[PDB]
Length: 198
Length: 198
Image (cartoon, rainbow over all chains, first blue to last red; front, top):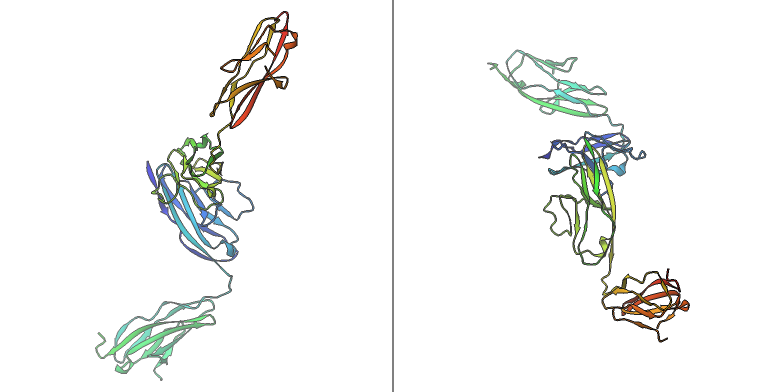
């Protein structure tokens, strides 16, 4: 009496070769839809309660999950999750992309860069920069493209730049830069210097 | 709560090209199984409630019937009817054989041939033979391989042989033969002749 509907559809997935992949396909209706899967273009249907092969790396659980173990590159393509009751049908496609395994350490990340500040002449400024990464990023700075720190400035040990006794010359854009053996990233912010500071 | 089960499975069918073929696949269970079909080896599933193609010659009714119209020879092969509930699954295969259309009139049929009779010397015998056919069969007879009717015997107009005043010589096997421009068929029976008749 109630057509099948999706609670959680499956979405696309890119994953390294040899890993295990699971696509949700959660469903509701009355009667309760029993989901099965089909690789697009394949004659094989994958039904929930079976022995099953056992040589097959594909299994479907009674909750609607399609688990594929030890994926190889021939498993890439589209997978259709499906359900048929006397009340209706629904299908949903999700794409599997199989990649090579690569020892690739991601580049550093700046979770919080400097923020825009208007400050007052001959005060202090601490423009912050919190980076994370493995290997661990070295922080460094630029002012309108050029390196930074003159006298008057010095980079702290968490990475915050420290400028003291500002003046109208010290306005402009300051760029945080986190770099490591795996990449660089940057995060900019403008700092204005008035005598007012407001 | 009640696994799907077949009430009427589909069976094999041989039919002339261009005709329409329907395979039953009637089902029971709880919840009520919704049948779908799949040509074996094909990625296409045929679901009950759909627009559907309209260019497709295959449709599945909500009762589980697979109708294929104007069959051509590429439709031959195996067709799988299937049903999945939260309670279980069932499949059943049936084979479609597509033939050429042939103007072939079937051969005659003998629906009732002579029956075994023990009769008494110098009585009468009417060994019956009811044939049917289009074109209509000519009936004729043999006694132990040789044609039949001597004097004493004559074929009636419905086809019954008529022998009178039997004797111990007239025992043996009598064969009815129905023949037409489309075939022959035969039906034998032994007739024994005692002086007793019992």
